[PDB]
Image: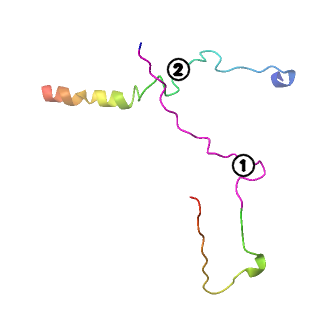
Amino acid sequence: FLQINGYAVSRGFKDLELDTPSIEKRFAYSFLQQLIRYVDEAHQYILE
Amino acid sequence: YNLEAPDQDHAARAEVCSGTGERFRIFRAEKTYAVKAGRWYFEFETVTA
């Protein structure tokens, strides 16, 4: 009924900015580099 | 004042610029030349890849 009367509901207009396009957000912030950083388990293992 | 350009973006257009009628063209032998028994061979040279 919205569509027939000509009203279109809009989804991501709120917080439409996400800033990623893989250009500003290099690498994988929370999987790849976070994994390789948590490999500091090895450094603390050496310290142990 | 140093400048950093955006990183290169891959091309995904797939160069599909043909007419709306055709995306590919099929060339076949005539139906009457259909083979139903034996050994058959033919050659296909590829001028482009």
Q: Is residue A27 magenta-colored?
A: no
Q: What chain does badge 1 belong to? A: B
Q: Residue furthest right?
A: A5
Q: Is residue A27 left or right of residue B40?
A: left
Q: Residue furthest top?
A: B1
Q: Is residue B47 left or right of residue A28?
A: right
Q: Residue placed at 60% from the left, 74% from the top?
A: B43
Residue type (three-letter) at the residue carrying disc 1: Ser
Between the residue at mark 2 and the residue at mark 1, the CA separation in whole angstroms equals 35 Å
Q: Residue furthest bottom?
A: B38
Residue B25: quadrant of the picture: bottom right
Residue type (three-letter) at the residue carrying disc 2: Asp
In this figure, which residue is indicated by the disc labeled 1?
Answer: B18
Which portion, as a residue range, is magenta? B2-25
Q: Is residue A47 above or below residue B1?
A: below
In this figure, which residue is indicated by the disc labeled 2?
Answer: A19
Q: Which part of the image, by quadrant, shows the C terminus of chain B?
A: bottom right
Q: Which mark is residue A41?
A: none
Counting from the top left corner in percent of width and height, residue B2 is at 41, 16
